[PDB]
Length: 274
Image (cartoon, rainbow, N blue to C red; front, side, top):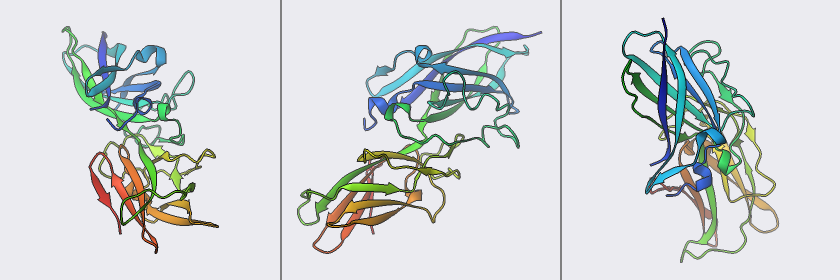
């Protein structure tokens, strides 16, 4: 005795600061679990399966079909669906051998990915939703709201404190302390939860907009090396201020003395300085 369901899945990347690249999903891993956290179904989707990015004004996302989710037929069955976007390998995902959501061995909560945020169009997103599979009844769509597992950081230069005029020079030469490792079951876009850490090199193209996974250690720093004449000076920021699913701007204020740095949380419209 066994019944088979097909689920309609909606992946929402955004609900106007994120670029089309940063909203792109090229591949994903979808996992379905029972009430006890046992994985009953999983599927790895790629660009031909994900289809096109649908957009209705302010909203944007992808539609997916989960064919052949097997149950054992006892009316309604409450389940949860977890989506990990842009972390798959060529033909499979690193999560394929994870048989439980929360467990001691081979679990999604224990899983750490070490592939750092570098490409805007291949940024990892994660989401989880709870639903009920209605037996011998017509299907209904289930939406999964995905968050950005990385933080977005834009260095916008050094300005004159007196008039707000942008100064020439003050080139970003180095960013040290960016994180390339992360947990995949953390969804709070307001608190730092990632305990995983490994060094993420600052690209040789020295970009002004760059990414990192969260850093929980209160003693870790993200250090910016900006030109101040002959030798570039180091400027440290608390690594735990950059939370996943947020966009930040680093601005400096020159006053013929030192530089007064400003950390802005763009979506929240908040600023933090000394």
